[PDB]
Image (cartoon, rainbow over all chains, first blue to last red; front, side, top):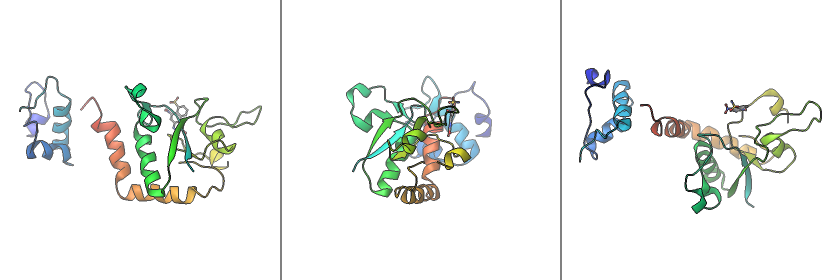
Length: 49
Length: 96
Length: 41
Ligand SMILES: NS(=O)(=O)c1cccc2c1c([N+](=O)[O-])cc1[nH]c(=O)c(=O)[nH]c12
């Protein structure tokens, strides 16, 4: 995942509900929280139904 | 008795909600200090009213008149019961 | 949090702040208003 976290040209996301989205929202690991704030703020939406 | 809270409009501590014209009393406001005031009241067991300091100041003593302005002045002169705001602990304020 | 000299309210107000700190609630509120509601990732 470290490769993803260091860039923005390739967009990335999760299901718009469920256990995978919740893992990122609550993580205290630096790399995972960096990924979370990107996903939360990205436009257009990186989440899927 | 309803506790009178003096505070100040500064983001993100206290802000008027976008739709405040449709709301009443404390529910007109949101922010860090709004949430903190609710937590303190719940733990201490009191009801309260958020009021915005009239002069928009934090608290300093006028060099000429020696009158305290701001939220500090509201407490010193007996006009409010508590200040919940981004108010810095300083020597001259701690004295009063 | 400030109050009126000698006010009885100030001894329970102070204990509440210390409790909210130890429970992690003050850290939760700072995160909410600065970061959860932040716009820059
Ligand atoms: N830069 S300012 O807006 O014009 C400003 C002017 C004067 C006093 C301030 C203040 C700000 N501030 O930065 O928001 C925060 C703050 N917090 C405290 O606790 C306190 O005692 N005084 C202040």
